[PDB]
Image: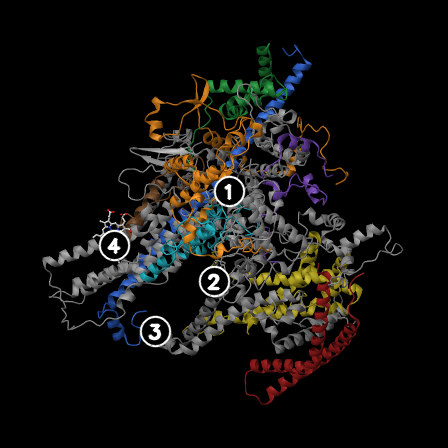
Chain colours: A purple, C red, E brown, H cyan, I yellow, K blue, M orange, O green
Amino acid sequence: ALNKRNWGYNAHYKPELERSMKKVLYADPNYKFPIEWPERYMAETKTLEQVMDEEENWEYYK
Amino acid sequence: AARVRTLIAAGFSKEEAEQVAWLQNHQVNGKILGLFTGGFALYCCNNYFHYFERYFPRLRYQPFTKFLAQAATVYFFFKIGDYYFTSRRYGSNDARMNGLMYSNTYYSTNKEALIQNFEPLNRKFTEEEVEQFLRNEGRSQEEKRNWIYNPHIHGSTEGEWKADIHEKFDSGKAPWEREHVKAKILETNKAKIDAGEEIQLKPFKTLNHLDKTGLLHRLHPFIWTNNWTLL
Amino acid sequence: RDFEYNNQDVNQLNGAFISLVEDEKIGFWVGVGGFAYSQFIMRKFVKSTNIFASVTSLFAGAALANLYTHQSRASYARVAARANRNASLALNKLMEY
Amino acid sequence: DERDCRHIDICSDYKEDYPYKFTRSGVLQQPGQMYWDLNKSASYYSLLGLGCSVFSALLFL
Amino acid sequence: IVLTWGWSSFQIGGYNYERFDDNGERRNTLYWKLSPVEFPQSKLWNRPS
Amino acid sequence: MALFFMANTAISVPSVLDTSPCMKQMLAYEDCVLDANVPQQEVIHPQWPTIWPRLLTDGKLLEFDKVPFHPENIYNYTYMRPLTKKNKQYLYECEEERFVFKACLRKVISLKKTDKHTSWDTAEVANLQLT
Amino acid sequence: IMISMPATIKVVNWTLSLVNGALKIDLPFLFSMSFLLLFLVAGFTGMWLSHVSLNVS
Amino acid sequence: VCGIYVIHVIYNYMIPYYWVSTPLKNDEFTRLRMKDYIASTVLEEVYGISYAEWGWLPHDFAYNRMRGLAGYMHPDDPRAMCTSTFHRKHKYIEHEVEKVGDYHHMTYPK
Amino acid sequence: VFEFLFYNQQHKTRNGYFINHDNLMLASLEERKKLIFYFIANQVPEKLDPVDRVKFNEELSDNLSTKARLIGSLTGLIGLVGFPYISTRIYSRPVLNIGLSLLICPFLYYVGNQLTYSVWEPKFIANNNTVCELSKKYNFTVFDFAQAKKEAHLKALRTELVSDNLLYSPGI
Amino acid sequence: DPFKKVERDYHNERSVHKHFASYPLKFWWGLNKFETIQGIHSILGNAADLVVSTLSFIPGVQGRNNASYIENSIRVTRFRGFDDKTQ
Amino acid sequence: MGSVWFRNRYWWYRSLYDDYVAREAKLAFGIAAFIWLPHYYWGIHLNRAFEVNFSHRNYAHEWGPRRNRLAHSLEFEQFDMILENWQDLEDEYAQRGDGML
Amino acid sequence: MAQTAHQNRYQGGLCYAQCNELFSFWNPSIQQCWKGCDFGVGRVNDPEGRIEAQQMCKRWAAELYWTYKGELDTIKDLRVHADMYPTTPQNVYRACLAGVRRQKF
Amino acid sequence: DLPADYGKMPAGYNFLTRGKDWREYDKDFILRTDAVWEKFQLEHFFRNYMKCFFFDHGLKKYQMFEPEDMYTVVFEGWALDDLITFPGFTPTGRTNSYQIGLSPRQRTVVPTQTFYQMQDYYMLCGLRFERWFRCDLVYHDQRHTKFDQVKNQKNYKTYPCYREYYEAQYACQDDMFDFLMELAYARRAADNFESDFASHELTTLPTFYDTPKAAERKTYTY
Amino acid sequence: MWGNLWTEASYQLNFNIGFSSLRSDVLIHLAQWQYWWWFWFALIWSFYYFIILKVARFRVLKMRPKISTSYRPHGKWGDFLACIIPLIWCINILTNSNLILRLIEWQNESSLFTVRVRARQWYWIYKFELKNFTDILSTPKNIGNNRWQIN
Amino acid sequence: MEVKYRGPSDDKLECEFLENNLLSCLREKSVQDNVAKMTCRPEFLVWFFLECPTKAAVYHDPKGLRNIFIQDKIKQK
Amino acid sequence: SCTTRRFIDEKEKLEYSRGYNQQELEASKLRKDFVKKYIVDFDTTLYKTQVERDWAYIAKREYRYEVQLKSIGYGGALANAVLLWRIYANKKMVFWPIPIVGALGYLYFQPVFFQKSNKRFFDMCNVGEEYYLGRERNKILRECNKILNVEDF
Ligand code: HEA
């Protein structure tokens, strides 16, 4: 437990500002980010038109 | 070197008493080592004190100067021991060099952290915090207490009390971490706020600022005598 | 509402405190008497200075008072140590978060 | 201002480039001949002269 | 010759140069925080190498 | 080298203290934008909504009249894509940070170098440069 | 790097033999001293050139 | 001492090179990797990093740790398997890193 | 084992530091309030308000703090009788005289301060209207007393730790 | 100003309040560890209390009331647990 | 240090070289310490300069591009404020078509 | 072990030592398993810890070599062969998973 | 946290900030006292750092020339050549100031660790070229109709030997590539496979890596 | 020099003593190694100060000559004892080289870009491969608080 | 690292080019990029903020900006 | 840089030669009090923030060299001159003059040095509001600016 460390995994942005709405959003266990940190740097294989259609047909977690 | 039972007599946990004893033992053992080293010198170089009278004639003529010189030697030995134990003596936090007192790293780090991280509560514990502590009788055991919500006894809503019960006991959020308690404390100590004095919500965590093993500061242990490897 | 001290420890402490007060009064009187007796005895047969006589008298009076107040003070100290240790442990276990 | 101590329009890092032109204060400043330094030298010389004269007067007795 | 200059000439020269020439630095720089530091003399002239 | 080769360890040398005016706000905005992961690269600028409004309309950043537009991959001509609603949704999560950064930049812009700055010569020495 | 081990022995032997003796200064002695002094610098230059980084530079 | 140094070169540089000579149908890549790793991982070439602050200054350690970690980027390097940890703070004093396993990127030390 | 000379001892036997929970095991409710107020104000006045701290410090000075110092000063001045105690026309030993005077005076000052404290502390603490008013205003609890005791012990440890290098402190 | 002696300042909260001159001068307080010395001090206090009651027979001064639990506790525990090992 | 550490110095002497330079060695050691002080001071100064240079290089690597981006953003924000003022002017021109002209 | 968290191989620990038993003496899979075991410190005893460790291992493997989105999610066999060199992102992910699985306490 | 849909993007949120009282964010920021001097220095540094171009007045446009020796800049200023127009750091003017790093390495067919013991990649280039030549000979003729060399680029498929060819080009130099290409042209005109004459393994020592049941050798485990 | 940023890094003047420029890390390390080697030889030279004076003052024929009765030498550990000084210098040189070399050697496969340098008769040729162009677009950017983004 | 020093130039021709770019950018972005031909180069506008800082004061001056807007409308007319 | 340090030292010498004024004298007294309390007599290791500790240690080293060491050197020179005169008088080596004149010279030149680099030392305290030392320095600087009617940084 003493030596357990993050090692740079899922390094999401930690807003220090008090008026940050995302903070409250980041508090929500049901909050969904735009993409997973494990896949944030993965090569995209989808087509441009398919990606545009999927992004247009997206719903907010809240 | 602190009569560890006496340290627990004042406000000190068993581990906190151990840390305070470690610091006091370091200081006292350094001073005692210096003083006792001074003792054998006078038991050995007493003739050397008399022989060094040809270079300094007044000593052979003024007897009190001999006692003054003996006291000076004792003080020099004590100060040498103190500097060997109670000085800064910063060094590299290396596993192959820690443990052996080539530096005073452990004691220096503990003292510096204690000086930097200690401040008074600057306020009185709220009655709700007193009540929460009063309701914390034996709730820290290994088995989680099955908190039963009785509407005739707990009132409110069954879920609301269950969430409140979790926040008070199961979640572990401190009474100093309660929103209502924080608001009440803000309302109360306004006079101190009239002087701009910050309010300390949590008491000074002794276990979070001192460590005889030194793991808190993350100083690697001696390579030859530690099975565990830090960091 | 607040924490309440243990019952048996409280009773023992009360008894020890009463005994200690009585022994303190008795020892003060005994020490005054011993100081007077020491002053007289030193002025009787001792060929020494008045400073030495007074120092001996004060030291002997303090020693007599301590001898009269040994058992009571020791018992009070033991009771206080046990009570304070128990109370401190309980309070630390209570306020620990 | 006479006591500006900045005779060249350059910062401490000297971000300006040579030739570094003089400043308005440096316009009036005379190197080593200012009133303050001249008065300091005058005071040193007066102190030395007063000491020597006192010593001579004591010897003249 | 053998002892004095062989252990003081280079250091004295470096001290005098840094004191009077500021390590031979060009004056028109932007900020010391983001500029290369012109170190003083490091190859000892009195040394054979 | 050796265990003691330089014979002097300059532990006094501290990390150079950064003195940018609104670096904290700018970095917070950048971190929020990175968490959002907006495909358009121009969004990194705080004034991006006022810089290229076509990004919020069609993504038509530049005129391709003379240079032909021949996209090959998804990561090609990324400046030529409108902001997707989901991305726009993620764009709302950083609005407060963007506004704070803009306010800080505006306040810095309002600053001037007046004559009262008598220590204009002694700036770097004040600005943690005498290391 | 290990080759310099024999040279140091030779320099030490020369220096030691030059001491605790009945010196009769001849023209030959000055030339031998000059040769030793010249050999002193050359060994240091060769040892410095033995460093891989310095040689590459 | 020289012969021991030579024997190490003899046992780890030439004779393995004389073992495999022609393209092989079965595990040619494995045999070549074994042969190369038998020679590319001599400790005299890698053992420096264990005590690096002796040759790397305080700020120099921070400046080089970024390149050093980036130096062993491609995992396909058996000799890199022998090099010491490039994720260590300066032994005397480290100016940048507070916690070793607290980084903002899985491949960037800061 | 002579830490009584190697460690600070003046702060121990004064300012009501001898009080502890065991004492509160026998005191009454109003007595508990008064004792808690006095001990908290003495050891850790930070937890109290500034105006109340000022008033309590003024009361403590008017009662024992200045009075114990005055009594110790009187005892030291009594001990200061005949500063040239060992003096002669042939030679007056300034070293021995100053040394004896210094050895006598501090002991007398300590004795006087201890006597004044042990005599007036019960009366001042027990029968102070301002102290009673402060106890009514505060009404510290047992948890407050425990926290204050811990803080006072930490402050005592800090005082010795602060004056650890009084000769040369480059800081490294 | 006494108010200046009440302000909470970190530098004030971390200032060495004891000079080297206090090392020797306050050294006499350590004798309290001695049982005989503590007893002598207590005897002096008791005699002073008797004289104080005798003088408190005069108006303006109240003697040591034997019904004060606080006073009794203070008198009986002023040196209850003195220990130079602590602090 | 020297002949003291050995139990038969004569033997020790021969065992090295059969030559004696002991007094030279002692005087040389004293003079060597007395001279070694100064080069130590100079090397300390030089090492401090080198460490400062390394720190400056690291900081420029870390803060340079960030400062440049911040300056660009400041210029863009000033331009945005000016553009907002010009847009207010254009709105006035829309409300005052030719009156402003 | 430049990417590992231990100064020496003997300082690697039993988990890292198990890495030596995992692959042959001629594969960087030893270093990969050492990195995986380092990623698993203080998370093996927790289920959510194991999940987050799998995510971290996937992230590290993706950072090492460029692979398509979700490609590592199509590994036919998570089992590893002793002769598996770190040639592919799938191999890297498998080695990291094995290193996480080998971390006790 | 008051509304249930807090954090959901407002509908039709133009994200415009026209006429916003910045005093609200004053409590959200802290400004150094030396802000004026810091801003002036930052502006000067931006003017003197990124501006690697010179505004020619004759064309009334910023122009640039390739980097040259400082003396050539100073002592040979009047003879400027190769002057071009300023294109800008980005087509849209975005800022490119950022610390640079290393992108993830591409998958490799020929492992560099096979012959990494040599500082010169001669044998490595040879082995990579042999592998690429085998792949090309396998997939030579179908490039024009079944690879990227097809006409309908909508159906273009990356050549199956693209990775090997790129790895070989990285391994070998220009002259080595030319010599290997000539040898490959000869071998392709021959259309002779290496296996069409392979006999070396018949005289090779037996190895545990050459057991009969190859699949039985790899003991897979997790 | 591109603009006001004077890219000229050497700028060495005539009759220079040391290296051309200390702008390179290798150059800084070499200078530090040389200075340190010059620093820690003191005692050695000290003996040289004492040996010369004694020989030139109490070893001549007219000043304290010595009758050397030395039939044979009987040294056994002299060479190994004196070899510590060469061993220390060798160790220092090897450590410095291994420190310098480890940062500029055996790191080819982990390269951000690639360029071919072909030296021809009286000329040099710099060849840039096509893939490098793609690598130009694939450079990660450390934006924000050490956050790496790939476009 | 070693960057020299050169203050803002404020050259008449460069200032004219920057002012033309700024006016075009204002006219275009005032329509929120909903114009006929995107002729503005934002990076160039950045130079306007640093190469003609004196003229920037006119941009920071309200009455001066109003007069400039009137002149620009007249020119566009 | 080194040029900046040389310029600062020369400007400080020139200013000390020009004069110390009255408002400037009061500001110097306040700055000296602040430096003595929060820096010179306060151990830099006690500060909460490690960065604050580093900056305070840098300032403390500057004070130890620029003020303490310089004053010690001046006092030592004065002591050497006085001891030379005394030894010339008695034709023998005395012992008291060295320490006595060293202490006197350290006491004397201690303020004068503190009088010259009063501003420069203050310039090493501008850590920022993020540090408690920074906040206190900002308050002190605001008071000095109000006194002097000039905007410092
Ligand atoms: C007779 C001539 C001679 C001698 C004796 C030597 C002796 C040595 N040489 Fe060399 N060398 C050459 C002639 C010689 N050399 C020539 C002609 C070349 C170039 C070939 C060409 O053109 O390429 C060359 C090239 C050469 C190079 C490479 C240059 C190049 O790249 O080509 C190197 C580097 O490793 C080297 C090293 C050495 C070493 C380490 C010794 C060692 O033997 C000497 C080191 C011994 C000592 C160190 C002992 C001295 C004793 C001391 C105690 C010194 C310490 C004293 C102080 C510090 C005061 N020599």
Q: What subunit carries mark 3?
A: B
| Amino acid beneath label 1 | Arg
Q: Nearer the viewer, mark 3 or mark 2?
A: 2
Q: Looking at the rendering, in which quadrant would you find the C terminus of chain M?
A: bottom right
Q: Nearer the viewer, mark 1 or mark 2?
A: 1
Which corner quadrant of the image does residue I74 belong to? bottom right
Q: Are marks 3 and 2 in contact (CB under 8 Å)?
A: no
Q: Are marks 2 and 4 in contact (CB under 8 Å)?
A: no
Q: Which residue is mark 3?
A: B57
| Amino acid beneath label 2 | Met
Q: Which residue is mark 1?
A: M105
Q: Please identify the residue farthest to the left as the structure is shown.
A: G26
Q: Above or below — where is M68 with respect to P104?
A: above
Q: Disc 4, ligand 1: is the CB inside 8 Å?
A: yes
Q: Looking at the rendering, in which quadrant would you find the N terminus of chain M?
A: top right
Q: Nearer the viewer, mark 1 or mark 4?
A: 1
Q: What subunit carries mark 1?
A: M
Cα distance in 3D space between marks 1 and 4: 47 Å
Cα distance in 3D space between marks 2 and 4: 37 Å
Q: Nearer the viewer, mark 2 or mark 4?
A: 4
Q: Nearer the viewer, residue C91 or C50?
A: C91
Q: Are marks 1 and 4 in contact (CB under 8 Å)?
A: no
Q: Nearer the viewer, residue F109 or N85?
A: N85
Cα distance in 3D space between marks 1 and 2: 40 Å
Earlier in the chain: of badge 3 and badge 2, it is 3
Cα distance in 3D space between marks 4 and 3: 57 Å
Q: What subunit carries mark 2?
A: B
What mark, if any, has residue G43 been given in the picture?
Answer: 4
What mark, if any, has residue B97 been given in the picture?
Answer: 2
- Labels 1, 2: one chain: no
| Amino acid beneath label 3 | Pro
Q: What subunit carries mark 4?
A: G
